[PDB]
Amino acid sequence: ASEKLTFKTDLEKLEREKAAQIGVAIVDPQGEIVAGHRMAQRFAMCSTFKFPLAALVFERIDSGTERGDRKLSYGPDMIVEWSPATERFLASGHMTVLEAAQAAVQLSDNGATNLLLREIGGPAAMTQYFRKIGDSVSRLDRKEPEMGDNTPGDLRDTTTPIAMARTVAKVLYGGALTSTSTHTIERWLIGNQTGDATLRAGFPKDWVVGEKTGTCANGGRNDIGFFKAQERDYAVAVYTTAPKLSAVERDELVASVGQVITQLILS
């Protein structure tokens, strides 16, 4: 109880001093709440939804409705802001399902994300997957980049910290995917290339952590994933809104949230 008070108080100090809102949920492998803050406030998902998108892809591979080596052809029309891998593979004319999903997860490649959306049936199909795994809250309404517009008050393209943390737990620990697909997506999250300065920078160096970042217009900076501490597994979702901070300061904010989480877990 005193440790939960310290957690709440320390997040609220960051919120006040940074003029920010911090949504956090930490859950155990079964989705039981360890701690949280603003945990049922809706926040724009930004690129965090690309982890659930990859889970959907793996579920279709597991079920036989998709193949990982299927070649997805495209032209320059599919290049959107921040498409590093899609741009490199453009001359060849395609990316495979698995190349696109790995680029979506580990580089946050937006063109690769839209290529997968085209293949799985668009935002409506992403939202149906959330519902299938018991998430009645998360919703994808648009493709990249407009799904990240983060207009104040807009419920499109949002989740809550608690819904998303429980979705992470279901995918990683709840048997949603084969052991093969679960291990592959977990290793992708550990090897994510875009999270070195966000949540994992605030965790002890010996914790196994994997995560997916997001950045939205209007000050959105998010990080969702899993960590293993003291032989316990956790799923975590952090959504923040800090319109007046710089990009680097928002990275520091999420890392500070990681430190506050660490202090709770250690205590």
Image: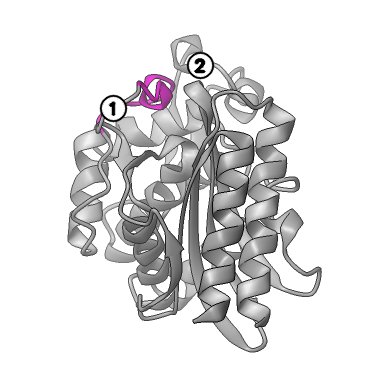
Identify the residue shown where x is 25% and y is 34%: 123
Q: What's the residue type where badge 1 is placed?
A: Gly
**CA gap, disc 1 and disc 2:** 26 Å
Left of 196 or right of it: where is 21? left
Of 136 and 54, nearer the camera is 136
Colouring scheme, one of rainbow, by chain, secondary structure, one colour: one colour
Residue 194 in sight here = no
How many discs appear?
Answer: 2
Q: Picture coordinates of residue 116 (x, y %)? A: 39, 36
Of 90 and 155, nearer the camera is 155
Q: Nearer the viewer, mark 1 or mark 2?
A: 1
Q: Is residue 150 magenta?
A: yes
Q: Residues within 10 Å of mark 1 (few under 14, many from 20)?
A: few
Residue picked out by circle 2: 80
* Looking at the image, residue 56 lies above or below residue 262: above
Q: Residue furthest right?
A: 205
Name which of mark 1 and mark 2 comes first in the sequence: 2
* Looking at the image, residue 216 lies above or below residue 263: above
Q: Picture coordinates of residue 78 (x, y %)? A: 45, 17
Q: Is residue 223 magenta?
A: no
Of 222 and 130, nearer the camera is 222
Q: Picture coordinates of residue 158 (x, y %)? A: 32, 39
Q: Tag 2's secondary structure? A: loop
**Numbered range of the magenta stretch:** 141-151
Q: What's the residue type where badge 2 is placed?
A: Val
Residue picked out by circle 1: 153
